[PDB]
Each structure stands twice: as structure tokens, then as C-alpha cells.
Image: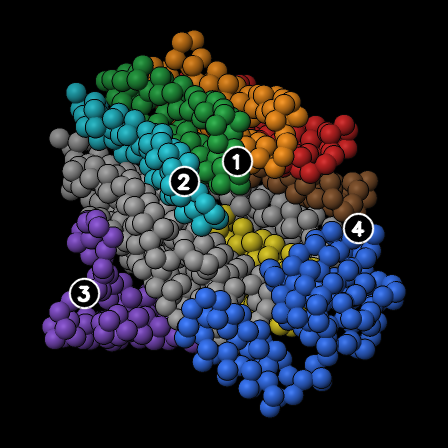
Chain colours: B purple, C blue, F cyan, G green, H orange, I yellow, J red, L brown
């Protein structure tokens, strides 16, 4: 089974291309929250609650893409 | 822990889909209004389909967090063979980020369930 | 170097200041030594001017136009500029309660004037 | 087999390239909602209804692309 | 038909690269509508009709590119 | 023969890479039109003619690139 | 064999330039629609630069499509 | 192998058209938005747009010469 | 073992394509913090907690993608 | 035939770097055209930074095109 | 070996594609530092410590990706 | 060695794709410096030191990626 072993190693590395959208997504939500907190006056909660929920939704694309890469090599 | 996390997350997703179907039987089913147009029934990637994707985020986060913690076996052989103090400082930040990720993951489940309960009664 | 001149008295007048933070329309920006020329509108917030050390004087401005010159000059022209200790907590609750009940209750400019008074009274009461 | 099994493993990895648009879409809608809520006072409904409905439309691209990748490996 | 069978599976995977333009289009149209509605008072109609019609035009590229991938499987 | 049949399936996959420019182009013109209509008073006509004509010109890249993929499959 | 299989690949990878030509018509239309509401660039003035600028940006899509059709 | 590599050389080299196509629209967006600010009309901004577009279009003409030479020489 | 050795070298290079999202993520959070600190006076604490915590969340994509490349080499 | 087939692909995939060199010449000219209308960066001043800035961004395209045409 | 020597040259070339993220990261921090220093006074202080510390974090992606290319 | 000579020519082409980050990086620092020097204040100092030092850091990715392409 030389064809199945060679395709399993390349599948885990080609599926890691989706980390650019998940990695830059956490910085996009943090850039608007840092620049908006100094504009008065949402600090405790308010705008702080949307940053925690928005970062978890953007990170779901990287967690779902990593499961298909680890299943082909295990 | 990996097999118990995927089975417990699948049972919580069925309760969100079953509760939305019961509330949409005593007061019709309005949901989306519209704007004098169509092509709304083909995009049924929410409500019922959103429960399979929201519950999968809890199981996928446990596999990614366990992979970073289990990588210390490969780095311990190189540090015991530059100085080795860089691996101790980097492992402390990953342990603090993994413990703090549980609060953000638990808050995402409560925020997702709040939008489904408010939309089912409107 | 500030020029906080109102329509009743002079606060800064002469150039003898260091830093000053005034709430503008976009955000809570603060002028340093020689700020750039960014003449923007001032909102109803707190205009604190730090005097060297911790000798800042919190002046609750009613809104104006914080104009900045290119030669290390900051002209903060406002209608009213009073301190935070010149307001009472019991008398401020009467004006905020009357503006909320009068909003969306009539016509003409009666309902539009009550919405602006309720937003300015809520921001000054939270900074005590 | 042989060529059919190797093409099925490589198809699930190349189909995961679409996660960059779906992953960054959750951060683009959250950045405008967090920065726009500081203008007083888009909190209850209004901006909250457009952010919840807009996030479901952007997430439909990642869920539809993941179904074609999982069907070829199962 | 060994070469035609292996090319059918890889053809449906490389054709899914167009989801980045269609997925980001739903968020770009919603970012201008959410930030513009707080400027008093783009709410009822006006900007509401352009948001529903503009989202359907940007989503046509994702549905057209997905038809070629399902037809080669 | 066998080499020409395998290249026909891959020809319609790599040619669909142009959907990112045509899909995001329909949302870029709608984002500036929705945020600009609430600025007083680009509503009736004026900007309505450039938005309808500009959306058809930006969508021509997706229809022209899709013709080469369907002709080789 | 080798020459016939390479003819189909010459029109697939060459069509990747549609992203620059497709987004170019939208970038010029976004600045013209937002700038026309500032009073009063309507007839001519800004209409001549948007019409001439769209034809120059669309030349990349027509030139790249000629090499794809000549080999397929 | 020599004849098969000449056809793929004119297709992979066409990936550089994204910078030349978007460059003509980036320079035209700043010139159209700056002309409505009173009064960059005669020359000034109009004369720099013709000379500035030649520098951005030089990358597309130089990249197209390498792709056409592999299919003819 | 020629097929396993050739695929192992390509796995470490194909998995390194994700460094663009992790490298630009640290600069995107630093650009908004540098421009916001000059407006006075979110410097000591306050806004310093979101910039330090935001850089660690964006760096998780680069560390997780690098673990799959080192394990296959 | 393996050495002759690799020479054609060495100049095709190397031409993908023209996106940064093509868009870089227009990004520097867009900021200079919008800033010159603010009164009065015309003669010199902004003209020296635009001419020197365009030559530095064009060095990446001339260096990448030399390795592709040398095959 | 012929298969081991061919994969080593392709590994060093595919790993060099990550320079777009490291090159644009140093320019992103330099663009905000050049525009932010004009407001005064974050040139010698304030933003001076953030520009030196922020450039070292963005440069870690280029040094780690270049180590796997030279070792293959 | 036909396989070793085929991978040597392909190594200089895939490694040259990193010029997009180095080419657009020098223009991002020049666009923010030209638009900030026209108002508060000059261009002979302050922003002059950041533009010269910022362009040398972003250009290091293009010189490092070109060395691995010419040596293969």
C-alpha cells in the first residue's frame, strides 16, 4: 500500500492551508476591540463580551480543518 | 477523554434542535420575514444544520488542545541531548492559554443557545 | 500650551500646560506636547488637562470644537466648562427622569430634544 | 482502488482551502459590529440582529465545502 | 478509464477554491450595512433593500462554482 | 486518448479560480452604494444607474471564465 | 499524447488572471459611487475618468483570455 | 516532454495579471476621489494619472513576453 | 521506502504555508495598538491586557501548524 | 528530455511575483495623488519621495525576472 | 538517491512561499509607526518600545520557516 | 541524473513567489510616509529615520529567499 501511505502524508500538510483565515481572524477582532476601547467608554462587558464570542466563532474554521488532517494520518 | 467528549457534545446538540421544533408548533413558524424575493429555502444551513457544526466545536477544541500538550515528549529529547530554558518559558504560556480557553469555549455555548431561544419565541 | 477659552471666562488662556484629554466626537483623544492639526467636534464629556504631575483639573465640558494648531497650540472652545465637584447627585436625577418620560410622547421638536438631553445626563452621572 | 484511493485522500485536503473566506468572514462582521456599537447605542437588537443573521450567511460557504471533502473520504 | 477516474475526484476539490470570494462577500456587504445603519437612520427600507439584493448577487458565484464540482463526482 | 481524457477534468477545476474576483466584486460595489446612500442624498437615480451598470461589468469576469471550463468538460 | 494533454492545461491555469480584472471594475465603481454623492460630480468630470479607467483595467482580462483560447 | 512543457509555460506565467489589473483601479480610485475635493481637474491629478499608470502596467507587459516566447520560440 | 521518504520532505514544506496568517496576525494587533496609544492615554494596563492576550491567540495557528511538519520529518 | 522540460516551468512559476511589483507602483502613486490636492505638495517635496519610493519597490521585479530569463 | 534528491530541492522552494507574511509584517508595523509619530510624541518613547518588540514577534515566522528549507 | 536536474530548475521558480511580500512591503511604508509628511511636519527628520530603517527590514525577506533559489 505505497499509494495510500504517500497520499496520507500529503493530506495532512495540504489541509493546513486554512490556518491563514483562522490565524488572521483572531487579530482582526482584536484590532477593532483595542482601537474601540480607547474611544470611550465601553470597557467592562459591553464590547468585551463580543470579543470573546467573536473569536470563538472565527476559530471554528481552524479547528474543523485540523480534524480532517489528523484523521488521515491516524 | 477524546471519545467521551464527542459523545457528550452530540447529545447536547440534539436537545437544541428538538426544543426549537416544539416551540414552532403552537405559534406557527415565522422565522424570516423577507423582502419581496425568494431563494430562502435552499439556504437551510442553520437551525437544524447549525446544531451539528456548533456541537463539533467542543470536540474539535479538545483534540487541538491535547495535541499541543502531548508535544512535550518530542521537545524533551532535544533539550536533554542553545540553552534549554527557552522550552520552559514557552510551555508555560501554552498551559495558561489552554486553561483560559475553557472559559471562552463555555461562553460560546451559552451565547449560541441564547440566540436560538430568543428567535424561537419571536 | 492650551487655549481653553469659553464664553464666560478663560481657563487656560496663557500657554502653561502639558497634556490635556478631551472627549471629541470620534473618540476620547488627548493632546500631548505639540499635537497635529486635527480640529474636530467635541462631544458632551469630561475635558481633563494634566498639569505636569498629578495636578489635573477635571472640567465637564458641554460640547464644542477642540481645534489644534500646527504651532503647539490647542484651542478648546466650549459653551460651558464646569468641574465635577460643582454638580449634585440628587438634582441630576430629576432632569434625567423628566427627559425619559417626555421622549416619544408628543410631536414637533419636543420628542427630539428629550433624546439628546437623556444621553448627556447619563454620561455625566457615570463619571463621579 | 490504487488511483481511486489516492485521489480520495487528496480531495479532502485540497477542498479545505475554502476555509480562509469563511474563517475571515466571522471576523469582518464582528469588527464592524464592535466598532459601530461604541457610537451609542446599538445594543439590543438593531445591530445584534444583523450580526447574527450575517454570520449565518458567511458560515454557509464553509459548511457546504466541508461536505464534499467528507463525502470523498467516507 | 483509470486516468479519468482519478481526475474526477481531484477536479471537485480544486474547483472549490472559489468559496473564498463568495464567503467573504457576505461579510463585506454586512459590514457596511451594520456600520452605516448607526448613522441615523438607515433602517426601514432604503439600505435594507440593497442588503438583501446585494447579498444574492455575491452568493451566485458560490452556487455556480459548486455545480461543476458535484457534476464531476 | 487516455492523456486527453484525464486533462479534461482538471481543465475545469483550475479555470474556476477566477470566482474570487467576480464573487467579491459584486459585494464591493454594493458596500459603497449602501453606505453612500445614507449620506444625503444618493438614492433615486444618480448613483442607482452606476450601481446597476457597474455590477454587470464586474460580473463579466465570472461568466467569461466559466465558459472555458464548461467547454472542456 | 503529450501535446494533446498539455492543451487543456494551457487554458486552465491561464484563467487565474480573472481575479484582477473582475475586482478592478468594482474598485473603480466603488470610488465613483461614493464620490458622486459629495455634490456634484455627475455629468462628465468624474464620469469620463470612470469610463476610461474601466477600459484600461479590463485589458488584463481580455489579453490573458487570448492565450487560453489559442491553445484550446 | 519539450512540447508538453511549452503549453504549460504560457498558462502558469499568467498568474501575474492580478497585480496589473488591480493596479489600474487603485490609481483611478484615488484620482476620482481626489478630483471631487475642488479642484484637481485640469492637469495636476489628470496629468499624473497617465504617467502613473505606465509604471503599474509595466509589470503586465514584461510578464506577458515570457509566456508568449515559450509558445513561439 | 522511496515513496515514504519523498512524501515526508514535501509535508514539512506544504505545512509551512500557514505562516502568512500567523506572521501577519502579530503585526495587525501591533498596528492598532501603536496608533491607539498615541491618542492618549491607553498605555499602562487598561489596553495593555487585550494586546498581550490577542497576540497569544493569533500565535496558536502558527504553533499548531508547525507541529505537523516536524512530526513527519 | 527532463532537463529541457524543466526550463520552461522555471520561467512560468517565477513570474507570480509580479503581483507585488505591479500593485506596489500603484499604491505609492495613489497616496501621492490624494495628498497633493491638500495644498501644496507639487514641485519637489513629495516628488522626491515618490520617485525614490517607486525605484525601491521596483527592485523586486527586476531581481525576480533575472533568474527566470537566465534558463 | 534520485527520489531523495528531487524532494530536497522542492522542499526548499515550497517553504520560501511564507516570505509574504514575514515581509508584510515588518511593513505593517512600520506603516503605523510612521503615521503615528506625526501626532507627537511617540517617536523616542511610547511607540518606540512597541515598534521594537512588535517587529521581533513578526520576524519569528520568517526565521522558523527558513530553517526547514535549508535543512531539506 | 535526470531527476536531480529537473528539480534544480523548478526550485528557482517556486521560491520566487515570495517577491509579493517584499515588493508590496516597500510601497506600504512609502505610502504612509508621503501622506503624513504633507501635514505636520517635514520630511528631513523624524519620519525620515523611520522610512530608511523600515525599508531595510522589509527588504530582508527578498534577499534571503533569492539566495536559496540561485543555489539550487
Distance of label 1 from label 2 (alpha carbons) = 20 Å
Distance of label 2 from label 3 (alpha carbons) = 32 Å
Identify the chain of the residue marked 4, using the numbered disc in the image: C
Q: Is residue B56 visible?
A: yes
Same chain? Circles 4 and 2: no
For image coordinates 79% across by 65% down, the residue present is C5
For image coordinates 45% across by 45% down, the residue present is F41
Describe the element under mark 3 as helix, strand or loop: loop
Which of the labelled discs sits on residue L59, or is there none?
none
Residue J41 position in % (x across, y down):
73, 34
Q: Residues within 10 Å of mark 1 (few under 14, many from 20)?
A: few
Residue C42 position in % (x across, y down):
65, 63
Count of labels in the image? 4
For image coordinates 70% across by 68% down, the residue present is C79
> Would you identify the image quadrant in which residue C57 lies?
bottom right
Describe the element under mark 4 as helix, strand or loop: loop
Identify the chain of the residue marked 3, using the numbered disc in the image: B
Query: Are the residues flagged by discs 1 and 2 in contact, CB closer than 8 Å?
Result: no
- According to the picture, the residue beneath numbered tag 1 turns out to be G40
- According to the picture, the residue beneath numbered tag 2 turns out to be F29
Distance of label 3 from label 4 (alpha carbons) = 59 Å
Residue G18 position in % (x across, y down):
38, 30
Query: Are the residues flagged by discs 3 and 4 in contact, CB closer than 8 Å?
Result: no
Q: Residues within 10 Å of mark 2 (few under 14, many from 20)?
A: many
Above or below: residue I6 compared with residue B47: above
Describe the element under mark 1 as helix, strand or loop: loop
Above or below: residue F58 compared with residue B78: above
- According to the picture, the residue beneath numbered tag 3 turns out to be B30
- According to the picture, the residue beneath numbered tag 4 turns out to be C70
Describe the element under mark 2 as helix, strand or loop: helix
Amino acid at each position: 500500500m505505497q499509494l495510500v501511505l504517500a497520499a496520507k502524508y500529503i493530506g495532512a500538510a495540504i489541509a493546513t492551508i486554512g490556518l491563514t483565515g483562522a490565524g488572521i481572524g483572531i487579530a482582526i477582532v482584536f484590532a477593532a476591540l483595542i482601537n474601540g476601547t480607547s474611544r470611550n467608554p465601553s470597557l467592562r462587558n459591553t464590547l468585551f463580551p463580543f470579543a470573546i464570542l467573536g473569536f470563538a466563532l472565527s476559530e471554528a474554521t481552524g479547528l474543523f480543518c485540523l480534524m480532517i488532517s489528523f484523521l488521515l494520518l491516524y | 477523554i477524546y471519545i467521551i467528549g464527542i459523545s457528550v457534545s452530540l447529545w447536547i446538540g440534539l436537545t437544541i434542535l428538538g426544543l426549537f421544533l416544539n416551540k414552532a408548533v403552537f405559534f406557527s413558524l415565522f422565522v424570516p420575514s423577507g423582502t419581496p424575493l425568494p431563494l430562502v429555502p435552499v439556504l437551510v444551513l442553520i437551525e437544524l444544520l447549525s446544531y451539528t457544526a456548533r456541537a463539533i466545536s467542543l470536540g474539535l477544541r479538545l483534540a487541538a488542545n491535547t495535541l499541543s500538550g502531548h508535544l512535550l515528549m518530542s521537545i524533551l529529547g532535544n533539550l536533554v541531548k542553545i540553552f534549554g530554558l527557552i522550552p520552559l518559558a514557552g510551555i508555560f504560556a501554552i498551559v495558561i492559554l489552554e486553561f483560559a480557553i475553557a472559559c471562552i469555549q463555555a461562553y460560546v455555548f451559552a451565547i449560541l443557545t441564547s440566540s436560538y431561544l430568543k428567535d424561537s419565541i419571536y | 500650551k492650551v487655549s481653553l477659552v469659553a464664553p464666560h471666562q478663560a481657563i487656560f488662556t496663557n500657554k502653561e500646560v502639558s497634556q490635556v484629554n478631551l472627549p471629541a466626537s470620534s473618540g476620547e483623544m488627548g493632546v500631548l506636547a505639540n499635537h497635529v492639526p486635527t480640529v474636530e467636534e467635541l462631544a458632551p464629556g469630561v475635558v481633563e488637562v494634566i498639569e505636569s504631575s498629578g495636578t489635573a483639573s477635571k472640567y465637564f465640558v458641554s460640547g464644542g470644537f477642540a481645534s489644534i494648531l500646527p504651532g503647539s497650540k490647542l484651542s478648546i472652545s466650549t459653551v460651558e466648562a464646569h468641574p465635577l465637584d460643582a454638580f449634585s447627585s440628587e438634582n441630576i436625577k430629576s432632569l434625567l427622569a423628566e427627559a425619559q418620560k417626555n421622549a416619544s410622547s408628543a410631536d414637533e421638536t419636543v420628542a427630539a430634544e428629550a433624546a439628546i438631553e437623556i444621553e448627556v445626563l447619563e454620561a455625566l452621572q457615570a463619571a463621579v
